Length: 247
Image 1 (cartoon, one colour):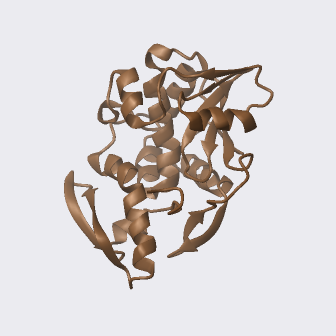
Image 2: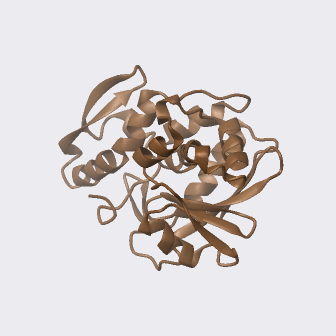
């Protein structure tokens, strides 16, 4: 289980946190040294809680699917919370066992449903250390009217950063303030399944992609990735997802 205090948070501390986050996630191997998560695992091990104390010292545990890095929900006191999707409910069976109540959320854990419930897309969502703090505050108070965005700001500032070290750095730099994610950041979040899958394919294909993953580079423009030679891929793709877990 991962843990991080917002109090005294820095880019270094966040990097450490995300590092700890990926460290919590088990892995069967590494393609290109990129840790390939453990696809096969007991449902109990398939999830790991992030303990996260916001600036206000309000801690809450976030239930992460370790095999896909996917957030399933979170806890706040005896009140636990989980997305309406059957993945979170399964998660609820293993995590927050002590939680006296598992709350099924009124929205699915996917960006689409989250953005709908939040009433605001991730492009307009704040990101950075204050965002995780804000997330914690909102989530602990579970303002369902807006908790959706808070979940998103938190998920990206954890799960997505855990996956992409590019996302990690961008968020982690925003110690003292926040910013709406770049199209590059968001592109990574989406491409994670495609890009990494093609890395696996490419691993047995001398590094050639079959399906060229269109990724948004930092300039907010699409760039064709046909080769694992792309440094923005190899240096930023911290965690590799399993073909069995992807599609």
